[PDB]
Amino acid sequence: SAKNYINLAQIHASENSKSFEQIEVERALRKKYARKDEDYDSMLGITRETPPELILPDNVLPGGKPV
Amino acid sequence: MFNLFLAVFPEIFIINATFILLIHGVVFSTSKKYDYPPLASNVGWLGLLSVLITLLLLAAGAPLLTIAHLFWNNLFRRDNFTYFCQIFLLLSTAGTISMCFDFFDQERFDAFEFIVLILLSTCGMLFMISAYDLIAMYLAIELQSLCFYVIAASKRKSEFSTEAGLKYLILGAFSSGILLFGCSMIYGSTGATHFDQLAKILTGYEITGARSSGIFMGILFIAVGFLFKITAVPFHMWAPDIYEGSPTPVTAFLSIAPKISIFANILRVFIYGSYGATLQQIFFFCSIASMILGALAAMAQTKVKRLLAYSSIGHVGYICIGFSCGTIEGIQSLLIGIFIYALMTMDAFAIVLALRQTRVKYIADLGALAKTNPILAITFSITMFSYAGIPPLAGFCSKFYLFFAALGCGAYFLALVGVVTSVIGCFYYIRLVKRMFFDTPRTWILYEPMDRNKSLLLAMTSFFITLFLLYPSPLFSVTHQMALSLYL
Amino acid sequence: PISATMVGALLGLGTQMYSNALRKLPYMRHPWEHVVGMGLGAVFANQLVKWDVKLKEDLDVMLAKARAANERRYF
Amino acid sequence: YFNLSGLILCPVLGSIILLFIPNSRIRLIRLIGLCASLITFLYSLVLWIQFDSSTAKFQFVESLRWLPYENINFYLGIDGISLFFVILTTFLIPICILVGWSGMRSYGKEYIIAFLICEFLMIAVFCMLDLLLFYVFFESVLIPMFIIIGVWGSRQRKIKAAYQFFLYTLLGSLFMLLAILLILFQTGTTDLQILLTTEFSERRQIFLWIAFFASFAVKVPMVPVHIWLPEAHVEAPTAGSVILAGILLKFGTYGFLRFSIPMFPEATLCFTPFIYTLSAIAIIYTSLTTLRQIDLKKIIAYSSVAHMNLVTIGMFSLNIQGIGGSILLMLSHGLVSSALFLCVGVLYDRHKTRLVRYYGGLVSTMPNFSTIFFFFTLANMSLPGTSSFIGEFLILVGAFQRNSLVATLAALGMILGAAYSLWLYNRVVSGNLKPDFLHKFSDLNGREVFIFIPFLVGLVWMGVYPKVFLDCMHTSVSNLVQHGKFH
Amino acid sequence: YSLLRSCTIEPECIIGQHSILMEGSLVETRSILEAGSVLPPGRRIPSGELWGGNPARFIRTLTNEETLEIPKLAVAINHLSGDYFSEFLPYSTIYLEVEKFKKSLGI
Ligand SMILES: CCCCCCCCCCC(CCCCCCCCCC)(CO[C@H]1O[C@@H](CO)[C@H](O[C@@H]2O[C@@H](CO)[C@H](O)[C@@H](O)[C@@H]2O)[C@@H](O)[C@@H]1O)CO[C@H]1O[C@@H](CO)[C@H](O[C@@H]2O[C@@H](CO)[C@H](O)[C@@H](O)[C@@H]2O)[C@@H](O)[C@H]1O
Ligand SMILES: CCCCCCCCCCCCCCCCCC(=O)O[C@@H](COC(=O)CCCCCCCCCCCCCCC)COP(=O)(O)OCC[N+](C)(C)C
Ligand SMILES: CCCCCCCCCCCCCCCCCCCC(=O)O[C@H](COC(=O)CCCCCCCCCCCCCC)COP(=O)(O)OCCN
């Protein structure tokens, strides 16, 4: 627990310190990619991947789910 | 030259706007600059604006739209009945397309072809009401038929949507073939595809004096095809499955927009092309069967969409009561019933779409809904009572005047069967009521709040339903004028 | 007496607050659209009354024409 | 200048205003509901003063067009018969709000909204002269009372009571509606005055009268269908149990006195013996059934059935004595049954038993309630000087003007009515106490001791001087009995 | 001061102050937890039983009248929260103060 909360605190540090201009982009990206549609995306030939800013580090996952 | 098209602007404009929307969507759905934007809500709002503009064009052309009536005679004949029927169908289409906007972004269904197909099927329906010939009748039927065959199977992930779309396709193709075979012999035995000259060669001699085996059986096949089109018992082979499998906004557009146009079409055919009084019998038994079987079958259903399907079948029987009694009051009751049923169906499907945000499937999921959202519970209970025919609401007036029309023609058996089917019909409606007010299940399903357009439409319809009996004169006067305009 | 505006405006305000409550919002969330709804209800009620008058007179004309046409069979 | 329309609009305004305010401020909701009910009551009393009892034509009429042809329209209006029903239904509603005043925080604003909607709708029923729209409002009370019974009712059988109540008012109601449509198509209008002056076919009146009676034999607890009242009345809230036996049981009798007696006079004569037999057997059977009951609610629900059945004996005996006594006993029952059911409600809201054997010998503990209950069950006896006697004896006199057998059975009804009424009184208020399951219990507080004071004063005013009530109706009753009786 | 963590609370389960619920605790339906109660991980509270003390300790049974008051308490707290909610409107005007402060120095 002591070791895990150390890497848990990094996301809170990188989140509470975000600037307002970054927060606008973050909220826009979060709302834009809230839900997906395989049908229309496949029809257009494109795949909508989550942006890198919207990826939590694997060390705070329930035990590691990179996929 | 150009002024001869003043009678087709409410349709030319909608076609041009449909083309513009299709072009805009296809151009800007594949642009790499904007990264393939989800422009389904944008196209939907533009389509709603286009529908409003063509409604404004249609409403302000009442003195117009009857000019150059000789030039357009072979193609279509629009009059006061057609004017009001179109002005109501277009409003119903606008409401349906307006209450489905959240469906596009809540479950991420950004296919703008849905909206353009709604618009183009609406154009086909506008053709159907004005249609005054067998050829135009069939072509306008086929426009909406193909649009709905495409739309029903739009959601290509669920086995229900695809199978329901295929069943709708097969049933509609068979019905269209039956209707077209019926029209072929009526053309063969008399010529005169035009309705004006079809109503003049058949009025000369009654079917009782001498028997023509061609005209009678062609009329019978046309009636059978039309009853397939409106899914009237016993010609209800797959309608509940169609309504259950098809996406919720599609079913919302169905059973309101198609039925109005098809009923206007049946009115035009019945009044003119039927003088042997042989369609009274085919409407009589089929409407009775629809009443009885809808009432006896909707009580055994546990899902919501199936219940709405069987309620629609029952109300189709109630409306078809008006065909059997051919008088001014019969047609008036029929049209009033269609109007009230359309409003109540819009309200009920707004309710269903509201709870679709959390994937409501059965009737037990809406348990203890009076606690989480009491006001929506009250609205749903009021709409359900309006379906039931309880006096202090709209829907009771339609059933009332339908019964009055049935008793006017001396069809005393129609009144009795209507009463008994209403008695059983109210029972399972109140059964829906008990699970939604009184008994509280252990597990509660929480529904996220609604959006403004659905809420506004729902509030307007709810205030219309409750307060209709206070001031019902305008609807009655519209309907009396429409019934008489079939002849003068 | 009610002049078709004391009822239209009231229905507009009622439907505004009705739609406002269905979204689980405070009743007077946006009073500007409350005033808009009052005005819209008043306008719609006045238009409904005028259309009812026009429609009734046109219906009376249609009934007169139909009765005159039907009378011709006897004479 | 206070018209009939303002009385109808007052509950509507009270309900619309009540929806505007939220539910957190509960005190405002109850205060505004009570204020609206009381001002409606005062308006109803004001309408009484300015009532011409000399003329036979109807009082204030407000016509609002319904169909575009003015074929049928809201034709409001009161007469000698409809005035007292309006006063009674305006008087009972504030009592309904006041009984559940303590539990208002548990019920909410839906409770007062439902009760004010009921007041509006019930007022609209009694004071209108359009036969068809009277039918619309006649079973329009289905929705609000269904809500009242179901939402706040029994423990788990509340669902069945709602269904039996809703089912009994469907087949007969629509079978009446068929006759409504035949009348509309035959004559052309549903205006009451026009329909009175119409020559109906001799064979036609039988069918129409049967259809009318079928939908009124369910509201009035006749022999075939009267089992709903006991079960759906025990499985009902106390304020919903005081208007169910206070107003709804009057719809059938009032409907008989409005759209059955005048329009079908010779049909009434031809069907007279059948109604006599039904009412007599109902009285006897209900009297014998009610004396072996253990449910604290049905014991007087059957008394209500007996009184309502006795009403029809003189209501259908065409006579000035019979009909006058009919309405007098109707008002008397509307007061006494309401008082009895309020007593049962206060008894139940303390102990929560719904039995009769549990209570016993509580006179030493609640003397005020003992006296009030004694006076109410004393009025139920039909003592002269109480409300029930004048009306009920007038019914007996009027029926004995026509027939000598059936109403003797009606009088035999009271040879057991008084007996089981005092026996029922002596189950509870007499004997030694049983403090094995009656540990703690109190007497009436300031609210429910004052609530009976209007009942007491109205009861004694009925009993000692009913001339003022008979004064305003003798024109209307005499006009009713002589209609279609030229000679 | 309810120290909830990885718990599971069923309906009508009023919790007292200084409650130190550990992980895996299951407070079954219609239960009362007295102030200061600390239950160890894995311990469950039977329905209709109110517990108190420092450890998870059975105190006494419940009657229907006492049980039915929990929803009334919940709706009363809901009413108070509804009264408090109307105090502040959406989209607070504090940004004016920030803009004035920014204008007072540079931009
Ligand atoms: C939905 C619930 C309804 C609940 C309300 C029920 C309460 C009943 C009052 C309803 C109400 C408005 C309807 C509101 C509907 C709500 C809006 C719905 C949408 C909401 C967004 C109609 O009530 C009256 O309207 C009359 C209209 O003619 C009708 O009289 C019949 O008509 C003939 C036909 O041709 C018949 O042949 C004939 O037998 C009758 O004469 C009747 O309908 C009725 O008398 C109130 O009356 C209002 O309309 C008129 C009347 O004067 C007034 O304006 C008029 O304008 C000029 C005319 O152009 C006049 O020159 C001018 O003098 C006048 O100023 C208003 O000031 C107001 O009084
Ligand atoms: C339609 C009505 C016509 C008029 C009829 C009037 C007849 C009188 C009606 C009331 C009679 C009294 C019955 C009251 C219940 C009897 C038991 C009871 O509860 O008595 C009460 C009250 O006692 C009374 O009787 C007072 C009521 C008034 C009695 C006198 C009535 C006089 C007025 C009526 C007649 C006026 C003249 C006619 C008016 C025109 C308490 O008695 P306590 O002695 O205090 O016992 C104590 C209890 N414990 C031991 C447990 C502690
Ligand atoms: C009948 C008698 C009883 C009824 C009386 C009615 C009284 C008259 C009507 C009064 C209405 C008052 C309403 C107050 C004004 C609100 C205007 C707000 C408009 C608005 O905000 O724009 C959008 C809302 O959508 C919209 O609001 C547009 C969609 C509205 C749907 C209307 C459909 C009309 C066509 C069909 C008519 C019915 C035909 C039935 C046969 C944006 O919304 P947002 O900014 O909040 O956020 C996005 C959520 N998507």
Image (tube, rainbow, N blue to C red):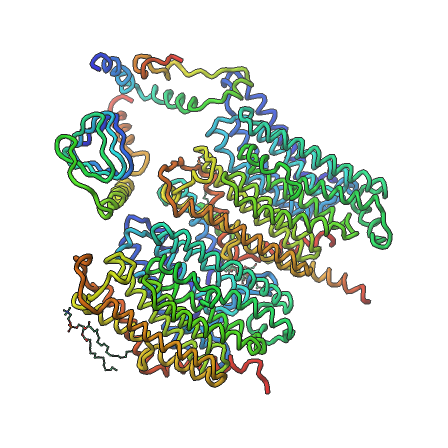
Quarter containing the N terminus of chain B: top right
Q: How many marks?
A: 0
| Residue placed most toward the observer, B197 or B416 | B416
Q: Quadrant of residue B113?
A: top right
Q: Quadrant of residue A4?
A: top left
Residue B424 image position (x, y, % from top left): 54, 51
Compared to D164, does B90 lie above or below? above
Whether residue B442 is visible to the viewer of this picture, yes or no, is: yes
- B175 lies left or right of D132: right
Compared to B152, does C71 lie above or below? below
- B227 lies left or right of B32: right
Quarter containing the C terminus of chain B: bottom right
- D287 lies left or right of B41: left
Compared to D136, does B210 lie above or below? above
Residue B471 image position (x, y, % from top left): 53, 57
Residue B367 image position (x, y, % from top left): 40, 41
Whether residue D320 is visible to the viewer of this picture, yes or no, is: no
Residue at 53%, 74% (x, y): give it.
Answer: D274
| Residue placed most toward the observer, C10 or C18 | C18
